[PDB]
Figure 1 (cartoon, rainbow over the protein chains, first blue to last red):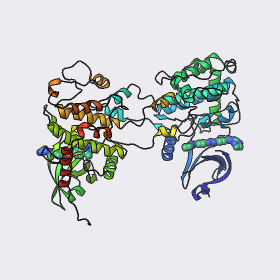
Figure 2 (cartoon, chains in turn brown, blue; figure 1 turned 30 degrees about the vertical axis):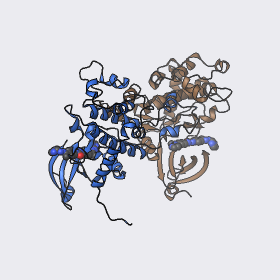
Figure 3 (cartoon, rainbow over the protein chains, first blue to last red; figure 1 turned 90 degrees about the vertical axis):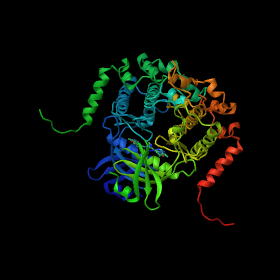
Figure 4 (cartoon, rainbow over the protein chains, first blue to last red; figure 1 turned 60 degrees about the horizontal axis):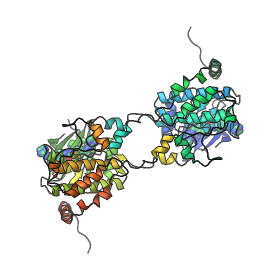
Length: 282
Length: 282
Ligand SMILES: C/C(=N\NC1=NCCN1)c1ccc(NC(=O)Nc2ccc(/C(C)=N/NC3=NCCN3)cc2)cc1
Ligand SMILES: C/C(=N\NC1=NCCN1)c1ccc(NC(=O)Nc2ccc(/C(C)=N/NC3=NCCN3)cc2)cc1
């Protein structure tokens, strides 16, 4: 059964997806919520999500630590982005841009606040409505990590008389862990624009691993002919194998493909619609 | 002042070294102890040290979490190994071997139990008496780390469709973090045998960093002429720059230099002397 403290505040309803996500109604307000059930690092995910405040990142409404974990969240009526890209379905380039812009803003906000998501995937991008133009929110912070003062920094404060060479070599590449999120964004954007994954074991002899470490994405010219050169250019700068040369979220946001004032206006318009609100002075 | 709970059990006395280490007497037994004062990860060090049971690893007797941290430990009357190797003083090769054998046993025991020390240095090797033949104990677990289930293992359980190349590349070298302890042991052994450090900014133009990552130790043939070829051979196998080719503690313990039954008998003899005891059946 559901725990009593949850039943106290919420009436539970039908499954929305699957881990498992259920529809519920908050008794106090009679408004719909979603309740993620995680069968029994969740404490950390909760703590991370409670501190973050961004319109493209999902907010926690409540939490119950019972026989399983129950996380109450805002209901995202559009479901998962995954459902929009399966079956080689693909979005209009304009829609890809709106969604990707928001993903970039979200991930930029995470990285500024010392958080790496580490599991960015279409399944973890939720749409706020069934309309094609809508807000997206990033979810599922179960693999996420907090950037802080490292043991490396502490190690490098002394003289390395006794220090191993591999530690000194790792200084070259440290502090670029956040770049794994930009690679994922790149893969997501590729999928959204083309309707197929860049690295896959479908109709090829190269191993998935070897595809990825070489950076050799599967390019099918006629799927891409309809897509703009600027869109593909950005994809190329995100799917760079060297994490230090890979585009950051800031660099992606400055890319020509995202200098689209129509898209940006539509995003601001959707934000205003969402928000309610409170009177202001002057 | 000292905290009341400490004063309750112990009478405090003179400084033994410096962090700071004081002599004290346990009131109950009238026997000497050492009290490490760490001015305000210690919780973890305590938890690690409480679980470990080896004659060459220092034991915690008591702990007080007051305005500073106070860790009560067995008194090691010989002091630090550092004091035996400063001023280009060097130990008899036979004594180096006895001490190094014990360090190896200690570090082997740590690695079998999923602990890496990460700060092995002459300062953290304590001698049990002022006699040249004595027991040693490794101390100071403030930088130590617990090997466990990694985020890498979890990441590799799914299909890496969205996974970044650098993660896949790091699989090649993961799980060799323990090898930094073997490099330190190598540096320690070098110092003990020769009376000088292998990597240093003394009378050279090569940077310390460049000395270490190239593995080019400073070899002065006439300091070493008196040292056996087998001793130096082991040093060479520990100061290997590739962490995967570096000798492990097991490989070091199988090295010809440590197949010395006289040395091993002396170690067992010193162990028996230390222990007291309890009657046994049959
Ligand atoms: C509108 C909709 N579907 N529409 C359709 N379906 C049925 C009938 N109509 C919908 C379907 C699924 C979701 N899922 C969701 O929000 N999921 C979600 C999952 C996980 C998390 C979090 C924070 N997970 N964290 C966690 N996962 C593993 C370990 N950490 C947040 C939201 C939201 C909406
Ligand atoms: C016999 C002796 N000196 N003799 C001589 N001197 C004066 C008069 N005669 C002596 C001197 C110093 C020590 N130190 C010691 O045990 N130190 C010790 C230090 C730290 C720790 C630990 C567990 N530290 N952990 C901690 N350090 C930093 C963060 N974590 C344990 C033992 C022991 C014995």
